Length: 9
Length: 8
Length: 212
Length: 222
Ligand SMILES: CC[C@@H](c1ccc(O)cc1)[C@H](c1ccccc1)c1ccc(O)cc1
Ligand SMILES: CC[C@@H](c1ccc(O)cc1)[C@H](c1ccccc1)c1ccc(O)cc1
Image (cartoon, rainbow over the protein chains, first blue to last red):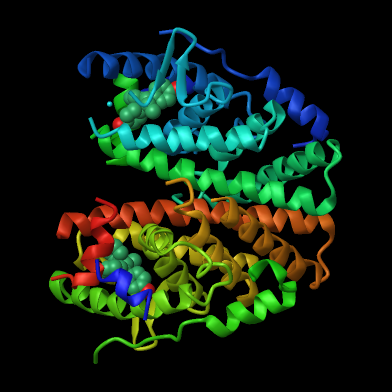
């Protein structure tokens, strides 16, 4: 899930 | 509709 | 509409429906049969909810909130039975299930939430009444809508009455009020999800066809 | 951190974290959804950044942050739609250059029943004269609440927002009784926002050219 990446950056 | 009769 | 909040509670408590008794295909038959007989008691209970008979609208409110009212009743019955759901005194089921295994957990979660909050019966009957009047109020005419809000406001006052007469501070009253009503949002969720899987007497399908 | 702020500091943080009003490109069944999915996709990117600026959200586990966003994303989209459609009765303002009516909803099948509930919620916010400071509180509540039973820290943050809501109403002249009644009225609407989201989610899965993120969000409700 790309949502993990957005929430970390 | 069934709900009509029972309510009355 | 002109009842004291003590008289409000007394009216709702006295109007309470009784707790009825009752593989994969057999258990659905039990729940379907049980809910169908509960619906009969709910309708006559709804007639005893203050302000409900002052409407026409009654059919619509019940068609939208029937599964909600059934679920919050279930959750209320399962409150003192951790990890399990008390559909009937002779039907106590836990997690140990096709697709409603998720709904069970949400019901268990809701029941668990009622437990730690130490939900009172006086508060329960208020919430159940709120669900009835609120769930189908923006799907309507507006002459009755104004009256419904007045009844909703009255039940809100009754809720705050109970908490104040329990020793809770003014802030604790607001907080508990919010906590309670926020749970109704989850009940709407469980109802919609439960209504989804449902898609079997004539009445139970008349209610079921309304959410198609 | 969120626990240790004033009600005024809580409001100011929420108002400052507010996402901007995006525009769409410059109908039919495929074109309508295209503009909506494109708008929603760009809104979601801002929402994720808005979520991280909501007090007590970063203090949660990343997994929990994903869970809450996936459960509330359409609610948050809808309550934002409803809010900015207040000053346009009978119409839904998706974008400043995308104003739609009830008849225009008839292009996407099954979408007109959602539009009616959205307008009704909007006219309700109108009738209540919902304030912006109250709107940002409701939106934060939706974020933290909608997926909490699917926790101990979240319930304390929710209580903080409840304190903040009462604070706004007390600082507006409303009596104690009027504060409880308004608070209750606002939170009951959240039950309907949940209902609209569920019905909207249903029709989206019935249609599923959605983006990867928008499809990841929808698959969470599958
Ligand atoms: C949670 C169990 C209910 C249910 C509702 C929807 C489903 O897809 C699966 C189960 C069940 C139910 C309700 C309506 C129709 C079938 C099953 C029920 C709920 C409350 C109650 O007091 C008695 C039974
Ligand atoms: C109600 C409009 C939304 C919608 C949601 C579900 C549908 O089946 C049809 C339309 C919509 C939406 C969401 C996701 C995908 C498509 C459309 C949306 C909502 C608010 C907003 O600010 C931007 C778009």
